[PDB]
Image: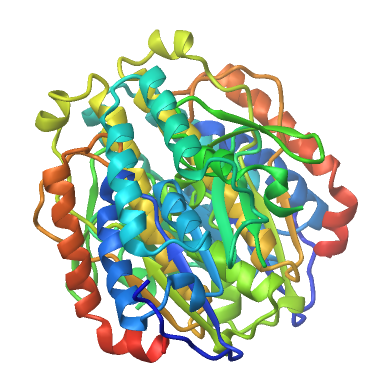
Length: 303
Length: 303
């Protein structure tokens, strides 16, 4: 490929954290494409660790398997909007199962080229379950099952049942309920497991952007339970932003860049419902612009 | 009063963190009544700092104003179930406004006898706003307005508009959306503001307990938008439990006791809707039992 630039090793732990957000990760991919092109290497050759939640876990997993961002974009375009276009629990659940199997096949957490964390929510304990790999990885679960769990947005998708290698059966739902912004769990991994000093950590947290809130009049035309749909989206946004604020309070001294800017267009449905590829494709340009507003600091962070 | 026991000062920072939970804080009060009676002094004479969110902020504020738990219980019984009994946005909003004015009148954050933090959620930035006092306190806002904001569970209550002393107008909603379990924000206050070492901190986090999840059949009889009601409750529970897990990951070395046990009765509606004083009064005994299962460690933590 064209990404032939090589970087020497140092004692700096470079961490990438990708928010969930329905099919709006086209924004995320626009940011990531510019970071990749800036660096001249696949992202796994520069970052030590990537965390992702829900559809951000799709991107994180492909990064950790060594994909280039244009390849991720092709896979994302051909599978993620179809999931969000579903309008029944059966259709949503089967569409997501098909995505997971088709995109990740039988890759496991022993197949990754960098550190990875994928966040889901445990139904019974209401606490996170984080699938990890490096170099029992992922609790013995396939990447497809872990990403599927990370994306299982009950009550609109079915809960995802997995059995760990130790034989424990757990029901899981979308990780956005506990960590749609996974950055604090990534920082915990860098500080508590990888035993890195705060000064030696660099965190890039890429969101999906912020767009005009859909109003009840619009949601009522595309969803019979529009209030639940609106509540899901607003609580997801609050958890995403408040997690960022909690990070800034507790870890002032961990160098961090968060890229998730606010735009007045496109007008979209919620993350659960939006699948219009015309609107979603415009988010790539918005992500590129968000990179451009931070390129000098991103250069000094990476490189 | 009967609470005449006196404690000497030491270099230990004793922190109390109270979860929100509708009218289910009868459980919280049962735990607190036993801690008070164990200590033999009003809680403000032993704890340095109390944080609360939503109806837990009602209890936190009364503690910080110097109330004894039996007095708090009387105020809670006469005002909080009436709020939750409301079945319209207008009725809920007026009931909460009446609670705030009647219970706190014109007390300000300069009137507290200990450290206090009360958490609300900013509507536009989707990030916490924490009203603080010790000894511009509370951003110049009254305790009544801060507690009201902490409890304003939009979309079912109106958002609460406040103007800070610096002249900034902010719209606020219930703090449970960002920190229904406020413990991490309390730890940030003890470590980042009060500059306490982790070894010198003692955290008691009292919840409202965990009870059987209400099913759609029951919610459909008491709420026209039952799915939104169920989603609100489940997301609130996940934020409460996952915040506790995040604390345990990031602050292994801060001594902490969380008291929020699981029970099979009473069968109740969600936090938003439950107002049956018969059921709710039984939660006091459950809180007393939860204290009893931890009394030896609580003695060594306090005292």
